[PDB]
Image (tube, rainbow over all chains, first blue to last red; front, side):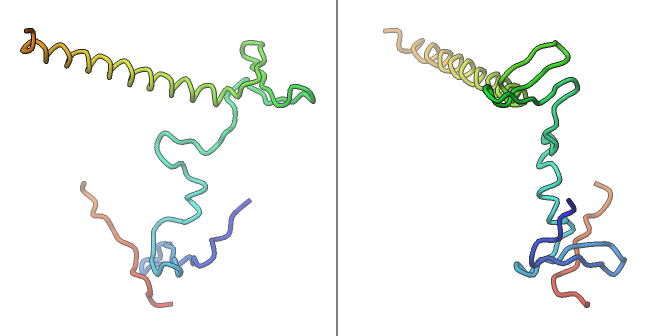
Length: 118
Length: 15
């Protein structure tokens, strides 16, 4: 569905005929369609569509509930593979925080007590 | 950058 502008917003044209948007609630103007907040990715890493990748299929069973089918590997799983993938990203970053922090603290405990070997 | 940033019209332009 094509959203209408939010209440208080108005589409306008500048002296050159370029479209811009007027926000009457905040008495401001913008080149940015305020509907872009819902339809454009937030960053270059974001993706608005949640559609599953090639070969994956959402499925349902009255006892198990929602689950997922991977036609690529001929397997099924309960966990959302999108969530799984994100968490494996997250886990790799967190593992590094822990490893790096431990390394840095060990390096500093050594550097210190070279003058406190005593 | 070689193109200058163009700001939108101020609030309250002619209708």
